Image (tube, rainbow, N blue to C red):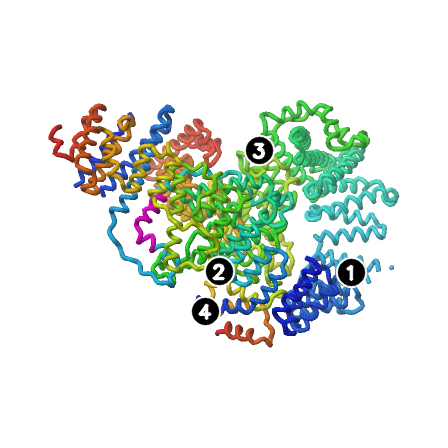
């Protein structure tokens, strides 16, 4: 399961690669770049840029992405509720990153679903597959979880294959 | 009454020679000294606070002795661990600590060091929530890294003052081994992100893959890209505009040596602890590199690769704390740590031929020598036992406790002459 | 960014993906940055091209609709929202928007009506829904609008905005008598009385009627009646303005209040108006004192002490004012209201008087001896108002400050003031969390269980169906357990705040939210649910919102409870229950206490060996290392818990094991339990005809009772710390002993 997961996610990163690299080319904000590096499933360069842009704590936090530590998951979500109940202002991309640490980035109450309009469906699916709750789910039911949140274009065949894969039963 | 003391120690020896395992002797010696440490400490002349600390020290010595000799001597050799390359770093760390006794000893010693570390009382009136700067307006982001992204002028003074209280408390807890309490404090004091940082301490294990620990664990845990984590933390530790205790924490976690502002207040024990931690960290990461269980991507930054020897750490920490270093039971502490112990026995023996000036010493060395030859027959030279007991006995006489001299006699035919 | 940053990125992805389809699929992400660079004729064409290839994306379609909204092209913007809505039905907010825009542009078509119906069922009775209902009607007509409001008020009588509109419609037809009439009948509504904007409307519509030609012509009999409501409105409006509004606005409201008081005192008499003036007079000073303390908080230390000195006098004046003559009012509703406010005055001013007097020794005496002088009256008018205003018609300057009691309040009186004033501010968790904190510094504890009984009547102490967390099984225990955490949490949060920078000294209006919005949302939900003022549509949502937290109040799966808070719950319920008289209540509170204990001890054992507790995920009650349990206190809790176990064993019938446990620990509390249970075994068997040998054994128990009560009093009189450990009052222990020995 781990092997298969790693190959799938390396491949998705192969596909979304240029899209995101373009987006990083045009960003004017460092924390957003850090997020985009997480979009390429590159935890280390996110951590590094964080470090460099003087965002050190975040940097540490980032290092958890891809270990599925449920403690960190519920803590990140907690921080998010506390902000989303008062929290006079939190940077738009730090909240996104915390939402990634929450393990349920659309499935949620600070939801990245609106990124539906800014990214390839495959890009977001990468987010579910990499963070998302890897251990608790089978590859199939995980992918299915994601698909349940987003309609794919009828005509797109790589979409179709994911649907047939997730459809299992 | 307190001029009972010798009885207690003598008493323990009685019980041992009479139920005809010897590690209990020392355990009792420890408790005995500790009990006495309490007596002189409670209500006392301020001439007693000194000899009270010399008893607490006494006690710690017996403890250290127990721990190390138990591990070294109760060594009955178990089964070797057979890893594969597919195995997690967690297992390799474990293997390292199993196979390398020299290094596990360092662990034992650090454990002892932590055991005896002071921690402040839990801060009272802690606030409802973090950086509550928010109220002044001006936190555009509520994340720890915001005032790092742009001038620290963002954070209110009182907030910094509280962050100071927190990070200092967490630091003391970390040096004491209280990692669970540190995580509890982080959680409960609305420092979730710092908590999360403290979670990176564990190497990765997966009970499913790393079969040989499918007992201790039911769920994967720990973090796979640890060499990264470690550079990430260390770099964070070097970034200024953080509270000195926070930086201190990250230093300790990265296997590094905390900043001057914090380190200046560390004593022999604290400092020694810091540097053994460094030895240890470095040695593990090297063990992992020699087995290709580190991935090149993670070598973000240079950390030092050359581990000190316990010998050298001791020498340096010594020269950094000469007064403390030279204290006669702490010399024994080091002597035990390096195993050069009969070495020092025979030594302080020849110092009877400014050891007579301090009272605990002549006693301690004698009872230690006794314990040693009990646990390891042959340990201390026959002569040295003779000389030591001879002199201590003559003090049992000077104290007028002839009553309990036969017990000490049970180690020579020289006893004939009493 | 600039124009160059975004138009240079054109060549960035143009050189990475040059085919027309991928060039157009980047249009949305091209348009993403032109919306940020203030380019709307350009951003429009970028998104519109991505829509040419990705015609089924609800996000892109909405984004163009939101962009056509900035362009104010209603026909185009609406259509865009429609496409995003028909693609994805979960976009509720867009169904409102469509309905919102259709009614604003043109109502002639029924399509605007249809979309409004859907918007209503997606947001049951939201504030915007009525707004749209009025907009649609807008397109001589006066009667038509009135019927809408009335039909709307039938099912939504607690809506602030709608009731306001009714007064405005009355005022538009210049039938002000009806405006005040409804205004008066509505001042009985407990919700509206708490609405800042409503009370503001109440103040105006009344004044307008006083000056109105209709007020004089009609009669001078009911003139007094309406005049009373103005003062009441002023009091409520003052309470609210002080909390939300800024320093300037609050002070300004005081002048209108003082003008009204001066204009009213001249009439006097012995009727509702006179009684109202009495109670409102007290409120004035109390709020004025609260107002004073607000200014000083921000100000320097010298002004603080002088202002707090001044405020202390104000609160004192208020507290002194006697309980208003309740019998003297026409109706049951009116008189109960007036008394409710009286309790509120004494309670709020009371705690303030104390918290200010705890600063120094008999600090209160000095305040009166120095500022009770008429010189203080001018120093009060000075600090509060600008001296330019005429000091003759200002009530503050003309009041006869005679014989200030200068007697600190008694706790027992304070408790009954609080309990009677729980319904003062509609039981807002703000109100209770404040009181709970004010009692956090006192040696006597508040009757929380009595507060909740005053709020949710006939809500069982413990629900039979404890197995599930369905919120039909909510119990006064759950609430009692809840408020305890809310206050235990609140105190720690404020403690942390001031540490970075007294917390007790803040008055109720001045301080901000003391609980987390999560906690407040729960209390407001369970309150609306219980009192039956929920919404058929929102019933299921409210119900689930409550359900979410139940499992934590009962320490079930994934409870966000720090061990210290659980222990606090356990002991706080034991001692709460151990002092109760009835068995039903004793059993329940002791049961829950044992329950929470049984959940902590596993944690304490791990903590006993200096390990780490697994920290929570988004806990309901914030964790704190300030109160993290230490090994120094573990053995005590294990002991204190074992008592709680024994107590429940005794109440259930396992006397043998209870005594065996009680006797094991020589604690003052174990005596009162040992004594109380030895006395019962004696009293029942003491006088019936029965074996003489048994009678001697029966007397023997009564002899043990006497001894244990004497051990309590002997150890009690000697040491004060033991007096506080008594599970019941000392005088109660002595009371039993008198009867025990006369037996």
**Number of residues whose C-alpha sits closer than 10 Å to that of mark 1, classed few (under 14), some (14–19) or many (20 or more):** some
Query: Which label's residue is closer to the chain start, 2 or 4?
Result: 4
Q: Nearer the viewer, residue C212 or B117?
A: B117
How far is mark 3 from mark 4, CA to CA?
70 Å
**Number of residues whose C-alpha sits closer than 10 Å to that of mark 3, classed few (under 14), some (14–19) or many (20 or more):** some
Q: Does label 3 lie on the same chain as label 2?
A: no
How far is mark 3 from mark 1, CA to CA?
55 Å
How far is mark 1 from mark 4, CA to CA?
58 Å
**Number of residues whose C-alpha sits closer than 10 Å to that of mark 4, classed few (under 14), some (14–19) or many (20 or more):** few
Q: Chain of mark 3?
A: C
Q: Which residue is mark 2?
A: A66
Q: Chain of mark 2?
A: A
Q: Which residue is mark 4?
A: A4
Residue A105 in the image, given as x and y percentages of width and height: 56, 61
Q: Is residue C186 visible?
A: yes
Q: Which mark is residue C135?
A: 1
The magenta span reads B95-111
Residue C384 in the image, given as x and y percentages of width and height: 73, 33
How far is mark 2 from mark 4, CA to CA?
15 Å
């Amino acid at each position: 399961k781990k092997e298969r997961h790693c190959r799938l996610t390396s491949w998705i990163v192969s596909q979304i690669g240029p899209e995101i690299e373009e987006k990083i080319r045009n960003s004017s904000n460092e924390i957003e770049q850090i997020f985009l590096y997480l979009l390429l499933n590159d935890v280390v360069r996110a951590s590094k840029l964080a470090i460099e842009s003087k965002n050190g704590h975040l940097s540490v936090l980032i290092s958890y992405l891809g270990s599925n530590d449920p403690r960190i998951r519920d803590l990140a979500e907690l921080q998010l509720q506390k902000w989303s109940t008062g929290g006079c202002s939190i940077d738009k991309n730090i909240s996104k990153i915390y939402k990634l640490l929450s393990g349920s980035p659309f499935e949620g109450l600070f939801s990245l679903k609106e990124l539906e309009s800014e990214f390839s469906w495959l890009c977001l699916l990468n987010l579910t597959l990499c963070y998302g709750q890897i251990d608790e789910y089978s590859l199939e039911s995980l992918v299915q979880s994601h698909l349940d949140k987003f309609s794919l274009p009828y005509d797109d065949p790589i979409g179709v294959i994911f649907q047939l894969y997730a459809a299992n039963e | 009454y307190q001029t009972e003391r010798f009885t207690k120690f003598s008493d323990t020896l009685k019980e041992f020679k009479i139920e005809q395992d010897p590690f209990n002797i020392i355990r009792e010696f420890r408790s005995a000294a500790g009990q006495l440490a309490l007596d002189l400490a409670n209500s006392g002349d301020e001439s007693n606070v000194i000899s009270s600390k010399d008893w607490e020290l006494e006690a710690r010595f017996w403890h250290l002795v127990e721990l190390l000799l138990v591990f070294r001597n109760a060594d009955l050799d178990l089964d070797e661990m057979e890893l594969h390359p597919y195995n997690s770093r967690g297992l390799f760390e474990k293997k390292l600590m199993q196979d390398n006794k020299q290094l596990y000893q360092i662990w034992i010693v650090m454990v002892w060091l932590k055991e005896n570390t002071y921690v402040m009382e839990r801060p009272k009136n802690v606030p409802t929530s973090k950086w509550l700067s928010i109220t002044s307006g001006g936190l555009k982001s509520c994340d720890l890294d915001f005032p790092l992204r742009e001038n620290t002028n963002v954070l209110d003074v009182k907030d910094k003052e509280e962050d100071h209280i927190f990070f200092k408390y967490i630091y003391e807890l970390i040096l004491a081994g209280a990692i669970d309490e540190a995580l509890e404090e982080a959680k409960l004091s609305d420092n979730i992100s710092i908590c999360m940082i403290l979670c990176g301490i564990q190497e990765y294990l997966n009970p499913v893959i790393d079969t040989q620990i499918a007992n201790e664990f039911n769920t994967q845990q720990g973090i796979k890209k640890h060499s990264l984590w470690r550079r990430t933390v260390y770099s964070l530790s070097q970034q200024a505009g953080l509270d000195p205790y926070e930086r201190a924490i990250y230093s300790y976690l990265s296997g590094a040596i905390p900043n001057q502002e914090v380190l200046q207040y560390s004593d022999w024990e604290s400092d020694l602890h810091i540097h053994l931690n460094q030895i240890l960290q470095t040695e593990i990461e090297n063990y992992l590199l020699e087995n290709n269980q580190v991935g090149t991507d993670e070598l973000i930054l240079p950390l030092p690769s050359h581990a000190l020897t316990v010998q050298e750490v001791l020498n340096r920490v010594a020269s950094r704390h000469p007064s403390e270093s030279e204290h006669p039971i702490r010399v024994l502490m080091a002597s035990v740590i390096l195993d050069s112990l009969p070495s020092v026995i025979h030594s302080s023996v020849e110092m009877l031929l400014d050891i007579i000036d301090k009272p605990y010493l002549l006693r301690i060395v004698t009872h230690l020598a006794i314990c040693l030859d009990i646990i390891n027959p042959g340990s201390v030279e026959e002569v040295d036992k003779s000389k030591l007991i001879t002199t201590y006995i003559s003090l049992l006489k000077l104290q007028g406790l002839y009553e309990n001299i036969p017990i000490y006699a049970t180690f020579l035919n020289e006893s004939d002459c009493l | 960014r600039s124009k160059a940053d975004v138009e240079r990125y054109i060549a960035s992805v143009q050189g990475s993906t040059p085919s027309p389809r991928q060039k157009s699929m980047k249009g949305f992400y091209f348009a993403k940055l032109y919306y940020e660079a203030k380019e709307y004729d350009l951003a429009k064409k970028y998104i519109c091209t991505y829509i040419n290839v990705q015609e089924r994306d609800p996000k892109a379609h909405r984004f163009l609709g939101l962009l056509y909204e900035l362009e104010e092209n209603t026909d185009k913007a609406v259509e865009c929202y429609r496409r995003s809505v028909e693609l994805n039905p979960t976009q509720k907010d867009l169904v409102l928007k469509i309905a919102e825009l259709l009614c604003k542009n043109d109502v002639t078509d029924g399509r605007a009506k249809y979309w409004l119906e859907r918007a209503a069922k997606l947001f049951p009775g939201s504030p915007a829904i009525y707004k749209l209902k009025e907009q649609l009607l807008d397109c001589g007509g006066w009667n038509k609008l009135f019927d809408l409001i009335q039909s709307e008020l039938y099912v939504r009588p607690d809506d602030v905005h709608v009731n306001i509109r009714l007064v405005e419609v009355y005022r538009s037809t210049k039938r002000l008598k009806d405006a005040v009439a409804h205004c008066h009948e509505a001042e009985r509504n407990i919700a509206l009385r708490s609405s800042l904007e409503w009370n503001s409307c109440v103040v105006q519509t009344l004044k307008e009627y006083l000056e109105s030609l209709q007020c004089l012509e009609s009669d001078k009999s009911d003139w007094r009646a309406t005049n009373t409501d103005l003062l009441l409105a002023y009091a409520n409006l003052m309470l609210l303005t002080l909390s939300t509004r800024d320093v300037q606005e609050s002070r300004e409201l005081l002048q209108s209040f003082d003008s009204a008081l001066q204009s009213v005192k001249s009439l006097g008499g012995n009727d509702e108006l006179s009684a109202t003036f009495l109670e409102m007079k007290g409120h004035f000073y109390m709020h004025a004192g609260s107002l004073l303390l607000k200014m000083g908080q921000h100000s320097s230390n010298v002004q603080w002490r002088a202002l707090s000195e001044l405020a202390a006098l104000c609160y004192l004046i208020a507290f002194q004012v006697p309980r208003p003559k309740i019998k003297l009012i026409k109706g049951e509703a009116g008189q109960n209201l007036l008394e409710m406010m009286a309790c509120d005055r004494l309670s709020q001013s009371g705690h303030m008087l104390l918290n200010l007097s705890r600063g120094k020794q008999d600090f209160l005496k000095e305040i009166v001896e120095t500022f009770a002088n008429k010189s203080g009256q001018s120093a009060l008018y000075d600090a509060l108002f600008s001296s330019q205003s005429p000091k003759d018609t200002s009530f503050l300057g003309s009041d006869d400050i005679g014989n200030i009691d200068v007697r600190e309040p008694e706790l027992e009186d304070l408790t009954r003031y609080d309990v009677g004033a729980i319904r003062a501010h509609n039981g807002s968790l703000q109100h209770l969390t404040w009181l709970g904190l004010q009692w956090n510094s006192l040696p006597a504890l508040p009757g929380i269980r009595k507060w909740l009984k005053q709020l949710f009547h006939h809500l069982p102490h413990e629900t039979s169906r404890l197995e599930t967390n369905a919120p039909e099984s909510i119990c006064i225990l759950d609430l009692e357990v809840f408020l305890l955490g809310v206050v235990y949490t609140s105190h720690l949060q404020l403690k942390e705040k001031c540490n970075s920078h007294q917390p007790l000294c803040l008055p109720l209006p001045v301080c901000k939210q003391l609980c987390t919005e999560r906690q407040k949302s729960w209390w407001d939900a369970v309150c609306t649910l219980i009192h039956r003022k929920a919404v058929p549509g929102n019933v299921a949502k409210l119900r689930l919102l409550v359900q979410h937290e139940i499992n934590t109040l009962r320490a079930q799966e994934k409870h966000g409870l720090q061990p210290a808070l659980l222990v606090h719950w356990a002991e706080c319920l034991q001692k709460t229950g151990s002092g109760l008289n009835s068995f039903y209540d004793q059993r329940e509170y002791m049961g829950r206490s044992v329950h929470y204990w049984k959940k902590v001890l596993p944690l304490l054992k791990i903590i006993k060996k200096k390990n780490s507790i697994p920290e929570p995920i988004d806990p309901l009650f914030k964790h704190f290392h300030s109160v993290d349990i230490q090994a120094s206190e573990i053995v005590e809790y294990e002991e204190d818990a074992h008592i709680t176990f024994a107590i429940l064993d005794a109440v259930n019938g396992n006397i043998e094991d209870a005594v065996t446990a009680f006797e094991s620990i020589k604690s003052v509390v174990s005596y009162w339990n040992l004594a109380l249970i030895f006395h019962r075994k004696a009293e029942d068997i003491e006088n019936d005809a029965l074996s003489p040998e048994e009678q001697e054994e029966c007397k023997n128990y009564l002899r043990k009772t006497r001894d244990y009560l004497i051990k309590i009093i002997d150890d009690s009189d000697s040491n004060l710390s033991v007096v506080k450990k008594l599970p019941v009052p000392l005088e109660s222990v002595k009371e039993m002993l008198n009867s025990v020995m006369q037996e």
